[PDB]
Every structure is written in structure tokens, then in C-alpha cells.
Amino acid sequence: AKLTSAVPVLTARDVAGAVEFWTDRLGFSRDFVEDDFAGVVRDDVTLFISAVQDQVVPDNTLAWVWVRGLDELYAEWSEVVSTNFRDASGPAMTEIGEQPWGREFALRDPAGNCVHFVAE
Amino acid sequence: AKLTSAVPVLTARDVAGAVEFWTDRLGFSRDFVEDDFAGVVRDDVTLFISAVQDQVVPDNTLAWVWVRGLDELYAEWSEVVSTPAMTEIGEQGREFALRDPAGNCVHFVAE
Ligand SMILES: [Cl-]
Ligand SMILES: [Cl-]
Ligand SMILES: [Cl-]
Ligand SMILES: [Cu+2]
Ligand SMILES: [Cu+2]
Image 1 (cartoon, each protein chain N blue to C red):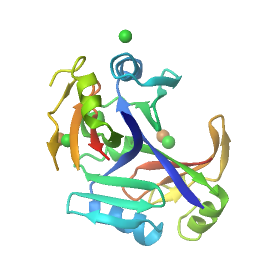
Image 2 (cartoon, helix red, strand yellow):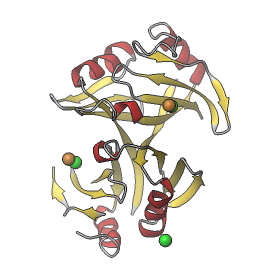
Image 3 (spheres, helix red, strand yellow):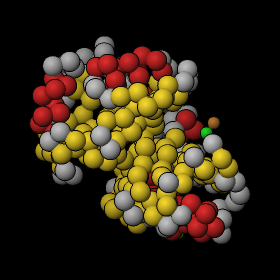
């Protein structure tokens, strides 16, 4: 057999709001959207979004995404996402950092999930 | 830019035990292991595992994985996991789901 790809599942109390942010703001496309679950895609990456009732879940939900052209993606999103991450009143992203595992930045979405984007 | 691959982050109150399950029982390899975070890998798929203090998180954590040879993977795991536990294979793609010791539920779908 061969395991070929994986799809992280972000969580949210407001599923429709999460889909709108990932698509209308970050440029992912809607693969499918149901009231309690959805799938969004950009290039070879699909992210699912699932409904939850306890905010503790997205508050502890993470995902990692590998990217060719990290600075370009950061530039695009910097136009529409705040870089004041310590202000958790809304979505925001960090600056690019050089972590042991790679050059990356992270973005906290409106639901609270933290998705890290790392340069290939 | 191009988004090339994604890595789901499973959650666990016991990261080491989750690593033990995914590697010894499910046949993933250890990519790296720290007390509060770890990475396991099989073929092109890497799963990260992060520590949490609230069991509600893994009890609501999901991930999907695509596979060539779904029936072979099911047969391999049916020798080490109760049918942690896994569902039967059913048509939705064709898939089965597996709940790990930490509570995460990962679905495996046939390409
Ligand atoms: Cl984080
Ligand atoms: Cl063992
Ligand atoms: Cl489920
Ligand atoms: Cu944190
Ligand atoms: Cu369920």
C-alpha cells in the first residue's frame, strides 16, 4: 500500500465564517461546503473544517503546510491579515522566523486554529 | 507560491504513548520525538502529535489520509487493532476510520 496525502481538519464553532476566511480572504477555493463540515483547497493542499461546540478545541488545533515560495505567500497574506499576532481579537499572523525545522510563519484564523506555513 | 503538502496535528494528553501506538502498532516511523510534540511518518504522509491537557481536544480531532491499497492497510491493522479501534470499510470514496489511544479519529480513504 502507499499513504499518499493527508488532510488536516481545522475546527470551528462558526464553520461558515471559517470557510469565508480561508477562501475569500486567503485565496483557497471551496471544494465542498456543508453546514457542519467543509473542504477548501489551494494547489496540492486541502484543509477540512469541522464543527465543534467547545472553543478549547480550536484553541488547541494546529496544522502545518509546506510551501514553495514562502515569502511570496506571506506578502499576499500580509495585505489582508494583521501581523499583530499578540492581539487575539481576530485573525493574525506572525513574522517569518527560522525555526529548527525550517523557515516559517504561522497564522491564527478567526476560529482560533494555528496553521504554520514552512518553506520547502 | 505553491502549497505542496500538509501535515495534520493529532492531539494527546500522552504524546509518548501516541507515538508508541502509531509506530509500533501502526507501522509509522519516528521522524522526531520530544516530550510535548512528535512527528511520525509513513510513505508520503507525516502526522504530527501535540500535547494537550484537555481530553476534549483529541475527542474532537480528526484527520483524513489517502491511500493506495486500502484493503491491504486494513488487513495489516486488523491484526493489531480491534474492529483503539477501527470501523469496517464502507462506501462514502471508500474508507475506514481508526480511533487511536489518545482519542483522535483518522479516516483512511482509497485513492
Ligand atoms: Cl502555535
Ligand atoms: Cl511498543
Ligand atoms: Cl468521526
Ligand atoms: Cu500556543
Ligand atoms: Cu464523532
